[PDB]
Image (tube, rainbow, N blue to C red):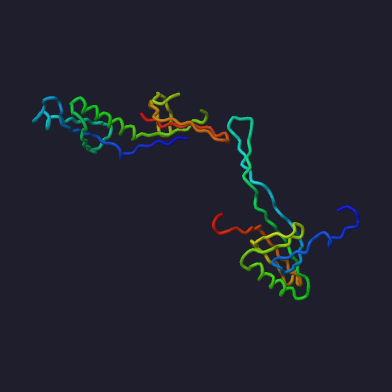
Amino acid sequence: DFSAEQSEDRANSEITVKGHRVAKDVWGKNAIVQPVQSVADSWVGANIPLTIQHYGDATNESLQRRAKFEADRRAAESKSVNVTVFHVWDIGNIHYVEIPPEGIFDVMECVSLTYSVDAKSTLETQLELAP
Amino acid sequence: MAGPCYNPNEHYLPASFKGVPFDADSSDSEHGRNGAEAEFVFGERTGYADLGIKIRSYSIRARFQTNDHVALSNAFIAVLESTGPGLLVHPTRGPVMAACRSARVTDSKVDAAGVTYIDIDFVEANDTVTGFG
């Protein structure tokens, strides 16, 4: 069995971050207004702006890393898949998939794994792939 | 049975319920015991566990042939509907306490006029105190 999905309610084309600096001696315009950075996905073809606040010591490198983390989370959440593979290695692996009816021909990284058994012989296993 | 010297009037008790006699025509019962059988996965051995006794149940059938059977039959239904359980003299199981659970009265005017059948379905009912023990 399988169930693909593509939800637009969990994507954003442009994410913005903000946050002050807390270094030994930084203040004024260099620690209040200066630290701003923007990162964009470019896969979504619409305008869905988002803005985030940073909880920490803002640095221009750290601003993008937080931005990328959100991008990977949103991207994965917008292509969740489920599969059942009957008979019963690890998560995060790399697999190839083929579902021509919807046209899946892309590499995937498994995000979850589950082994289930029953007294009536019903073995199964589930996956939560995402690219 | 064995031998020609049987006397059914001597081996079967006369039925009754709450003291009103009636003519019995059949006698069944159901007993048993509650199990918890379990079978594991990939295993060649099984298990079992006892959980207690199962509630009994009795079913009887009555026939009314005498003159004016409608009054006796109609008057007997007024006893099965009386509130609460009462003593029952099962033809073979002896005196037990039971409560009527259902009763279907069959009758016809052209197919069979002059005889009324009534099936019953009893359940064992032992009195219990109200303070949950």
Between B49 and B110, the residue placed more toward the observer is: B49
When asked about the image quadrant of residue A28, the answer is top left
**Viewed as shown, does residue A117 lie left or right of B87?**
left
Residue A78 position in % (x across, y down): 33, 35
Taking the image as shown, residue A28 lies to the left or right of residue B75, namely left
Q: Is residue A33 above or below residue B8?
A: above
Query: What residue appears at the point 79 percent right and 62 percent down from the top-left corner?
Result: B13
> The C terminus of chain B appears in which quarter of the rendering?
bottom right
Q: Quadrant of residue A110?
A: top left
Reply above or below: B38 against A105: below
Relative to A128, is A54 on the left or the right?
left
**Front residue of this view, candidates B108 and A120:** A120
Q: Residue furthest right?
A: B4
> Which residue appears at 66% of the width and 57% of the height?
B124
Q: Quadrant of residue A61?
A: top left
- In front here: A74 or A44? A74
- Residue depicted at x 78% and y 64%: B14
Furthest residue in direction left, as rendered: A28
Q: Where's residue B105, x and y in %?
A: 68, 67
Residue at 38%, 26% (x, y): give it. Answer: A109
How many marks do you count on the picture? 0
Image position, residue A4 (x, y; %): 40, 35
**Relative to B95, is B68 above or below?**
below
